[PDB]
């Protein structure tokens, strides 16, 4: 449902409009050719024009396919890749990897196949593209086209940029609206935080914290910020839409209560990956409970409520005591200084609750006051049942270790220590992260599973940063606005918008 005149809205500016862009965008290879979606495509498309470069983009594609290849078909896929790219007389031959590394790769295949066999060649290839190919791309019309896309990304976003639909629930201050970007037709979930209620509470720092944690996290398993704009009355956060309901509803209304272990395995795997992405930004979630794990239209989950998240400075501890009764780690209950450990405690509570259909310290059919629940979180060992394999018991109690120093995932190794746990022994994370493992439950599309003071002006300016680069570029790709608009001249000639001669 794109706006009637969307090709006018996303109409490319003339390349002469982007000179300021050209002089300020940092020419970092990883940013312009990989991390940024549209930059990645444009650079790949530049390599589509040089015969020598084309072979390298095809190779990196086959390596990615190899990484998520099932363990049994690794030898087959490896032998294929070997005889297709790294053999000398091939029409598609990787020459910059050097015969000194292609002979090594032939030995890796002579022994057990590993999912990392081509990692050495892949870096060698990127080491080559960082040089002459990248700097050629910079002086090509595809980087001028990239600057045109950046120019659109920077355009101001406003209330008129969106199309509000229905009320998607309510929370602190305001409610989740349902945005649709007029120009592209993509759906989102507004988060209208009312201005009069932020100032009345004096909670301005809490709004920017959430907005800034959201724009930095770039996870498949955490709600991502796409836009941040102000609309006179309220500040808005445009977020990933999740129409599949929350995990609490699926544990208790759709569950036994509870899930089969293998089903909870899948959700735990995706939640662990969410926490891992947050921890890369040394950010602690602290709100891990079933109602905050949402499902999407496909059945995948994302962590949603980041209102209690904070960015921990590197080499620092914080003091808080926040969250929900029953889902506060003991170090949080005691108001101690902690790091990321509360989230691995929450993961434990989630895995337990998914398998057993009740909390490990409160019975589903138990009327108990908070004093006893908290006392239990601090003093009693949770007990398991025949719904848990020995592996499931192990990870839950390791994650539910009262002492954060001895708790799983709270060492220097981080989330990797949790992924190694025998509970994920049958879980292939590369494939999960690549979205290749089918979710265990697919929501049906049709279903519904549920003043003038300038001191405020400086706060609105730091919030209303507008578009978020990576989410925005991905939006252009999903809606096919990129495929449709990213057209050049007939026979690789410069289109009018990229020729500095006739504007
Ligand atoms: C599609 C959808 N998604 C999500 C939530 C989020 C999501 O997708 N990303 C997020 C990121 C962040 C948060 C988050 O932290 N928000 C907190 C609380 C907050 C803070 C401040 C504030 F001001 C407001 C909220 C939330 C989500 C929801 C919640 C729904 N909709 C429903 O469940 C509806 C459906 N409904 C109905 O009956 O059917 C209809 C015909 C469709 C109407 C009526 C009532 N239940």
Image (cartoon, helix red, strand yellow):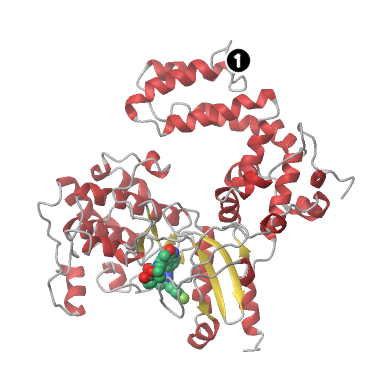
Tell me what residue is drawn at x 62 percent, y 83 percent: 456
Ligand 1 falls in quadrant: bottom left
Of 163 and 394, which appears nearest the observer? 163
Q: Position of residue 401 (x, y in %)?
A: 23, 59
Rendered image quadrant of residue 71: top left
Residue where numbered disc 1 is placed? 91
Residue 477 % position (x, y): 58, 48
Q: Is residue 178 left or right of residue 52?
A: left
Image quarter of the N terminus:
bottom right
Asked if residue 33 is positioned above or below residue 219 in the image, the reply reads above
- Tell whether 480 sits left or right of 9: left
Q: Is residue 317 visible?
A: no
- Residue, far left: 386
Residue 119 x/y as whole percent: 48, 30
Q: Is residue 318 left or right of residue 490?
A: left
Residue 397 locus on image (x, y percent): 20, 55
Residue at point 38%, 39% (across, down): 431
Residue displayed at 33% across by 55% down: 443
As drawn, which residue projects farthest toward the right? 501
Say few, some or many: other residues with alpha carbon within 10 Å of mark 1 (under 14 / 14 to 19 / 20 or more).
Answer: few
**242 and 342: which is toward the camera:** 242
Residue reaching furthest to the front: 4
In which quadrant of the rendered view does residue 10 lie? bottom right
């Amino acid at each position: 449902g794109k706006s009637k005149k969307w090709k006018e809205i996303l109409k490319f500016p003339h390349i002469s409009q982007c000179e300021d862009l050209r002089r300020t965008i940092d020419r970092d290879y990883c940013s312009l050719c990989d991390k940024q979606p549209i930059g990645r495509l444009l650079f790949r498309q530049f390599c589509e024009t040089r015969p020598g470069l084309e072979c390298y983009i095809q190779f990196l594609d086959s390596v990615a396919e190899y990484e998520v290849t099932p363990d049994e078909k690794l030898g087959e896929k490896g032998k294929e890749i070997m005889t297709k790219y790294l053999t000398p007389k091939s029409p598609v031959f990787i020459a910059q990897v050097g015969q000194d590394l292609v002979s090594q790769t032939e030995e890796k295949l002579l022994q057990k196949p590993c999912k990392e066999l081509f990692s050495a060649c892949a870096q060698s290839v990127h080491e080559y593209l960082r040089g002459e190919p990248f700097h050629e791309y910079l002086d090509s019309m595809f980087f001028d086209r990239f600057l045109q896309w950046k120019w659109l990304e920077r355009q101001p976003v406003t209330k008129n940029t969106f199309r509000q639909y229905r009320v998607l629930g309510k929370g602190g201050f305001g409610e989740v609206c349902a945005c649709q970007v007029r120009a592209t037709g993509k759906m989102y979930a507004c988060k209208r935080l009312e201005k009069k209620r932020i100032k009345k509470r004096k909670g301005e720092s809490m709004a920017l914290n959430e907005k800034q944690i959201l724009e930095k996290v770039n996870s498949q398993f955490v709600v991502n910020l796409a836009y941040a704009y102000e609309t006179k009355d309220a500040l808005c956060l445009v977020l990933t839409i999740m129409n599949g309901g929350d995990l609490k509803f699926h544990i208790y209304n759709m569950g036994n209560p509870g899930f089969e272990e293998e089903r909870a395995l899948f959700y735990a795997a995706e939640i662990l990956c969410g926490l891992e992405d947050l921890h890369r930004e040394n950010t602690v979630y602290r709100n891990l409970k079933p109602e905050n794990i949402l499902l999407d239209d496909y059945g995948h989950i994302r962590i949603s409520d980041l209102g209690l998240a904070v960015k921990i400075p590197e080499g620092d501890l914080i003091r808080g005591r926040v969250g929900t009764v029953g889902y506060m780690a003991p170090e949080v209950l005691n108001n101690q200084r902690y790091g990321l450990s509360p989230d691995y405690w929450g993961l434990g509570c989630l895995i337990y609750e998914m398998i057993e259909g009740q909390s490990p310290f409160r019975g589903r059919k138990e009327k108990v006051k908070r004093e006893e629940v908290d006392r239990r979180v601090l003093e009693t060992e949770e007990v398991y049942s025949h719904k848990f394999s020995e592996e499931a018991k192990s990870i839950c109690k390791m994650l539910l270790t009262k002492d954060a120093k001895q708790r799983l995932g709270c060492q220097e190794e981080g989330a990797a220590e949790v992924k190694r746990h025998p509970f994920f022994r049958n879980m292939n994370f590369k494939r999960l992260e690549a979205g290749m493992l089918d979710p265990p439950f697919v929501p049906d599309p049709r279903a519904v599973y549920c003043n003038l003071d300038h001191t405020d002006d400086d706060f609105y300016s730091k919030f209303s940063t507008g578009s978020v680069s990576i989410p925005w570029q991905n939006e252009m790709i999903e809606t096919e606005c990129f495929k449709e608009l990213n057209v050049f001249g007939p026979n690789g000639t410069l289109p009018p918008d990229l020729n500095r001669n006739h504007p």
